[PDB]
Amino acid sequence: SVASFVLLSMVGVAVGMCMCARRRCITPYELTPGATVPFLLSLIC
Amino acid sequence: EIEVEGNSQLQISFSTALASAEFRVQVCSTQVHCAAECHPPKDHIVNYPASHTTLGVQDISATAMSWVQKITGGVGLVVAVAALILIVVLCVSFSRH
Amino acid sequence: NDCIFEVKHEGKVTGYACLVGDKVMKPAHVKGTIDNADLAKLAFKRSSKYDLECAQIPVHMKSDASKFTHEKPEGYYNWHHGAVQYSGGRFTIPTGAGKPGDSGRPIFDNKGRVVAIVLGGANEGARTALSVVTWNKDIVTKITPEGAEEW
């Protein structure tokens, strides 16, 4: 039980960090009036 | 104690509770590392106390603990990827002003 | 010119929000809601590093959106409170031209294109520089003249 809980907690932490990194990367681009974004970042998101 | 002469082989009997018996034996201050996979007995109940000590919390698990290592390594790799991405994004945001 | 919207927290105007390109934005440091009920109900994206809240303009305001441009040469730009001098990579006006409470005012070029939105200013000597946000075509950047007071 504790091992499964720890693994799930680590997975959730990784997901949260990835979402936070994605939001921080996307924020500068959703505030520029030009609708410009690199295609690589679009594939990432 | 054993009686030894020349170049030969000697037989010893041992008992353990470990699924994977990895131990060392000293004979005349010479050490040998023995390793084996042990199988559970088929007789459920016996009339004599166990000759081996119980296994604790450190000398635990079997040789097929590599599943634990693999799962820990995979989850740690995922966590490391997430942390590396977060570090890169934070460094970019800190450098940018 | 149709880049003017009221924001109220006590019932008075506290800041300004506008229509540019394909999006609405307002400074996030101004308390209150948009006067237009159509715009205040939208879902806004909010960033504190640039102090801004933004959303997408509905279709029916395609005629209301103003033009924008990233290129910004040296010289004079125009806004509601007279004109501003952009030089040395920095917007300035002379001392005391701005007063607190006027934040949200965009800065326009000679063609009427928005190039910056003021958030504050700080006075050195006889001239006061402006802490605003502007945009490389890529990202929204903020210029602060070694610290400035909020409007």
Image (cartoon, coloured by chain):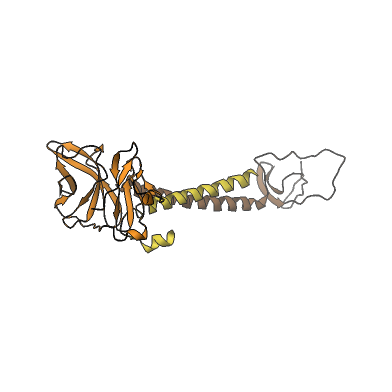
Q: Specify whether C69 is left or right of A20.
A: left
Q: Residue furthest right?
A: B47
Q: Specify whether C108 is left or right of A8.
A: left
- The one nearer the camera, C96 or B25, is C96
Query: Residue at 84% across / 46% down in the picture?
Result: B44
Determine the image quadrant of residue A42.
bottom left
Q: Quadrant of the C terminus of chain C?
A: top left
Q: Specify whether B70 is left or right of C8.
A: right
Q: Vertical placement of C33 versus A41: above or below?
A: above
In the rendered image, residue C118, in percent from the top left (x then y), is placed at 24, 45
Q: Could you say which chain is coloured orange in the image?
A: C
In the rendered image, residue C107, in percent from the top left (x then y), is placed at 21, 50
- The one nearer the camera, C85 or A40, is C85
Query: Residue at 37% across / 58% down in the picture?
Result: C58
Query: Residue at 85% across / 39% down in the picture?
Result: B48
Q: Could you say which chain is coloured brown in the image?
A: B
In the rendered image, residue B35, in percent from the top left (x then y), is placed at 68, 50
Q: Vertical placement of B19 versus C146: above or below?
A: below
Q: Residue furthest left?
A: C126
Q: Residue furthest bottom?
A: A39
In the rendered image, residue B37, in percent from the top left (x then y), is placed at 72, 52
Q: Vertical placement of A45 versus C49: above or below?
A: below
Total label count? 0
Q: Could you say which chain is coloured yellow in the image?
A: A
